[PDB]
Amino acid sequence: NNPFYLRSSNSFQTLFENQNGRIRLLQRFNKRSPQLENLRDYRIVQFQSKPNTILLPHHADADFLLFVLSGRAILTLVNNDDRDSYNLHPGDAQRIPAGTTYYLVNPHDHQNLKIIKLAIPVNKPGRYDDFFLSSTQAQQSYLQGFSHNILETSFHSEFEEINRVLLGEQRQQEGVIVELSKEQIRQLSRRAKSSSRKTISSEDEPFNLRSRNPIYSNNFGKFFEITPEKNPQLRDLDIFLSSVDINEGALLLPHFNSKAIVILVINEGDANIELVGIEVQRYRAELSEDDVFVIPAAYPFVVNATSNLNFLAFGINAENNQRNFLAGEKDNVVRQIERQVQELAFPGSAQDVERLLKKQRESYFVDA
Amino acid sequence: NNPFYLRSSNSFQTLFENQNGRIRLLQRFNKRSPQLENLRDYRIVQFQSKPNTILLPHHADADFLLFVLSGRAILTLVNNDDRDSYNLHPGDAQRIPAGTTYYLVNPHDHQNLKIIKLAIPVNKPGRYDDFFLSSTQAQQSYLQGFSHNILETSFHSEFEEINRVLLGEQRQQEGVIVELSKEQIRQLSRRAKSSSRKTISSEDEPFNLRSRNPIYSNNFGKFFEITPEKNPQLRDLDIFLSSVDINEGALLLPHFNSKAIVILVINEGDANIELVGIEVQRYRAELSEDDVFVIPAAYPFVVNATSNLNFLAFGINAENNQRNFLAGEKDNVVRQIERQVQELAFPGSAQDVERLLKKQRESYFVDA
Amino acid sequence: NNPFYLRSSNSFQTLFENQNGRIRLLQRFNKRSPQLENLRDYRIVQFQSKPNTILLPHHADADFLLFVLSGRAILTLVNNDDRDSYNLHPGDAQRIPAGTTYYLVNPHDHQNLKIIKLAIPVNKPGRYDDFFLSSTQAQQSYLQGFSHNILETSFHSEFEEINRVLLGEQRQQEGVIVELSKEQIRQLSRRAKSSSRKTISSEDEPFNLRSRNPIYSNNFGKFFEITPEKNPQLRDLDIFLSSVDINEGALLLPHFNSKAIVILVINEGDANIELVGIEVQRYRAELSEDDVFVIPAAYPFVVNATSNLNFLAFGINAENNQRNFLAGEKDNVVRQIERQVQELAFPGSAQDVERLLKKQRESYFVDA
């Protein structure tokens, strides 16, 4: 039983779901195993919506860091005196600060919109609520919290009028994800500023993870990553971003993280994973699509692509985190040790260990 | 039963009280409702003093942010090698860094001194202690912690000597708040550097919340605020101050704070308040003088002044916090959504909705 | 039963020990009393090794701040692409980023290597694990966590050849501290950069606490101290390091810390200690070598040196903390209070109190 493994059939809680989309919310990282207690302030949210759809405007008491896996979106954040629309593409990411009102459109005509966002609540540690402004068959708008009298006074209106317009106590929609006119979307999209190479380091607009050269890349996979060093949005959240692709039958050589807690999310494919932790203990698990395997800090682990494989990883506590490899040539730790220490470390000869390490000649991704 | 409402009668605990005033300590915010587990690191104190009294020198294991609600005071801070007296007036605010020995004088003849301070204990979370230097009838000087021999050694004297002067085991005051000589207050009161417009941004001297123009003001009320943006002393604790007048039968329009948890204390007047959380849930509560009400971030709330009303707000987690309103002209989100989305959100012609919003022609403070 | 006092003969727990030394791990600070809750994220590690010994390579999911109390060590950090050896002398401090893999060497022929290190665990709060690369009769190597297929696929070899070289399932050493050839230590000592007066403020190499002038130093004692202000490394951990010495029969004049929580580890000699908390409460404790006494912030406390003494102190919550002294000429707070308040503070004439406080002519360390 692998505590660092969250399947998908039956921890994701569906927050809303209709014929137009669904929003699921991963279970608390510490409700699973107290071993994950330093993640108690984090959640995973998965949003899927149909082509030509919107998410009705709303805010939450939590930062968000969202990542576009596939499809195309329009993320519009509304403020007290401004509005900002951003044209997200696959591999784009952006930060929705806490308390900001916003809506999500899927401007595509056939493709789906699969987004995953990392919630960081503000009031209750690892719990947060969703304030929908709109009054839908599926949710009351938070304006209906206020008394008639307050409402009449606040809006300068008889109740029958504010009710008949904003609330409606059928005239209202079915769900918080509704469908859009082509004509509508045609308007909504023509003022969305979009991700560019110039945004790698902007505290506002979205930056693309895969825009840059992958840190690691060879015939067996590619390792894209963005870190608080290069991105102010990720400096404040102090988290690192990385999305990495593995050719079926390759794998990511064993490695550990100096100081980062990593939340990987399986985007596509199948994969086997092996985590070790303390006389050592094997933490293996067989991950499929939409699964989540968390990898504590400084724990060595390996990723075996049992199919063509792409996943997203969130790196908690990522200021100056370093990746260390035990196999392969470049970034190998077990090959920087002084020889005499190598001798002393294992049962073998300085030259005998110098021989076994030099064997496997590739680095980062190697083939099964 | 509003877990965000702290009835002054049964939420305060007197700490030292007598003929010359009293000190009371608000209860832990988390012990009330676990919904407030992010304020567990904070406490509220009310210090009230009769005219021409002093608070005997002492210190705490908590950073203090004191706000003077009413009266005049001479705050003095004794360091290891320096002393710094300050002249506080109503509205003045200053920060007593933890473990700083300090005494409070009330130089007024007829007027009291009503202060309120936010406490951030350093040793236990939410719990702090007071180390009174004085040997009193209500408290032992903490020097009376040391054995006779260490004390003899430390001061270079006999014990009968050092007890007869500093401890006294009838010669010693009844409380930690004792009356003063005019001649004393004459002398104490002539070196206390006083607040001014050149102090809004000092690490050291206190700053006035109201020496600057409010951020909102109309005939029905005023909204004074200082943030970590303009203050170093606030930047550090990462808190905003705000002090707002609402005429009777006016109200603060329905709004929510993006990421700031607000601890508001009713200074003067009566008010009704309304909070919404999640199908929505009304959280009304009828505030009176000295009451406390807490408003989690991104929670919409409204404050209805049922008699001339002024209150004080401490905004916890206020780096880059935005106020959003839901009613009135200026700073209304609901009125910044793309219209076509307004069509989709409420059961009301985007035209029929543009009409309702525009109706209330005022902003921030409107009239019941 | 002083909760702030952790007796060494029964508050340590041994993690590894053999004929080549032993590693102890202090018990959890709050496990003892909830009163120390604010340290819960910290631990004390003690290490000591025979002459001519190496601590086999490992890493831990925790930052370490080690201090060389006594001996000469060669500290070698091994990165993915770099390697960094440091020649540590007594008084040298240096910081091991979590998940850094590193090995310790004791190059002396007769002397030891007594090192203590403060531990800040990443994943679980207050709990960490040592991941040892090395296949030893004591512990498995974490590469034995993985499974044969993955191990085979990783190194590009069969299993027998990888188990005969790195693991060995007789041929392997006995414990995680093994002895060295002189030839070995000789080669291995070739590039260990050593501390210097030009390291007092380097973010990398180790800095000596005593290489500067102390803050306090008369004929009865010395107070070496370094704050986050002067060291980038102590800044990131927000800590102060202070090595102080007290002659037999002198003491540290009673005093309290403004906002730092102090973890003092008794290094050499005996000492009587006394603490005061809250009606006051005496917390006296008779420390011996290797004991640990923790001092809540703004708790006044005196240290009596019953034999020739020296202790290391950790200053948690260090940024801008202030030592306030209750007796003595210099840094005495009680001698700063206005005279008229002094008159009002204690039962004694302003001149009768001015008199007692001028007696002790000396400052900080007096004689008993």
Image (cartoon, coloured by chain):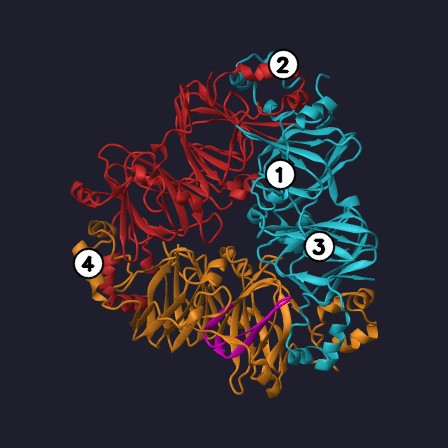
Chain colours: A red, B orange, C cyan
Task: Please identify, in this view, whether the residue under mark 3 or under mark 1 is nearer the observer.
Answer: 3
Which numbered tag is attached to residue C128? 1
Q: Is residue B88 magenta?
A: yes
> Can marks 3 and 2 be said to lie on one chain?
no
Other-residue count near label 1 (Cα within 10 Å), few / some / many at <14 / 14–19 / ≥20: some
- Gap in angstroms between the C-alphas marked 3 and 4: 72 Å
* Residue at the disc numbered 2: A352
Classify residue C162 as left or right of residue B172.
left
Q: CA distance from mark 2 to mark 1?
A: 33 Å
Query: What is the chain letter for disc 4?
Result: B
Task: Please name whichever residue, C160 or C148, is drawn nearer the observer in this view of the structure.
Answer: C160
The answer to whether marks 3 and 2 mark residues whose Cβ atoms lie closer than 8 Å is: no
Q: Which of the two marks, 3 or 4, is nearer to us in this view?
A: 3
The residue to which callout 4 is attached is B354
Observer-side mark, 2 or 1, equals 2
Q: Please tell me whether mark 2 sits on a helix, a strand or a loop.
A: helix
| Whether label 2 touches label 4, CB < 8 Å | no
Q: Which residues are magenta?
A: B69-94
Q: Can you give x and y, in whole percent of width and height, for residue C293 in the image? A: 73, 52
Judged from this view, the residue extending furthest toward the front is C197
* Label 1: element kind: loop
For mark 4, give the secondary structure.
helix
Amino acid identity at mark 3: Phe
Three-letter amino acid code at the position of disc 4 = Glu
Q: Nearer the viewer, mark 3 or mark 2?
A: 3
Q: CA distance from mark 3 to mark 1?
A: 32 Å
Residue located beneath label 3 in the image: C223
Give yes or no for residue B90 being in the magenta stretch. Answer: yes
